[PDB]
Length: 47
Length: 51
Image 1 (cartoon, each protein chain N blue to C red):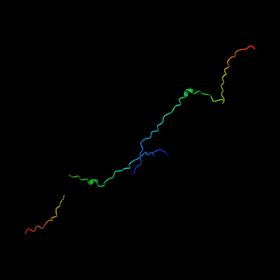
Image 2 (cartoon, chains in turn cyan, orange; image 1 turned 180 degrees about the vertical axis):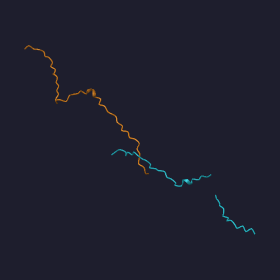
Image 3 (cartoon, rainbow over the protein chains, first blue to last red; image 1 turned 135 degrees about the horizontal axis):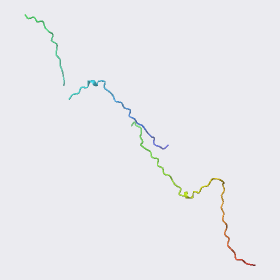
Image 4 (cartoon, each protein chain N blue to C red; image 1 turned 135 degrees about the vertical axis):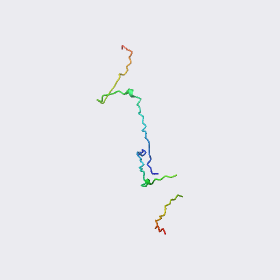
């Protein structure tokens, strides 16, 4: 009835976690970009 | 606030203790139950009177 209670193991259950998107990893150091509007060809009415 | 109290060691201090009389330790063989000893009383002489 007089001993201190003897602890013996802690563990820290731990797992890492993921992304499922890390093949989009683009590094760098407003930003914009652009595209061309279509120009369909034409009837050569040479008159 | 959520961990068990870890103790690290215990000691058990203990020292053996003597008797200071072990040169008196005579040894029997554990047979019989009575021992006995006896001396003779002293008896001084007398003057011898021939009457």
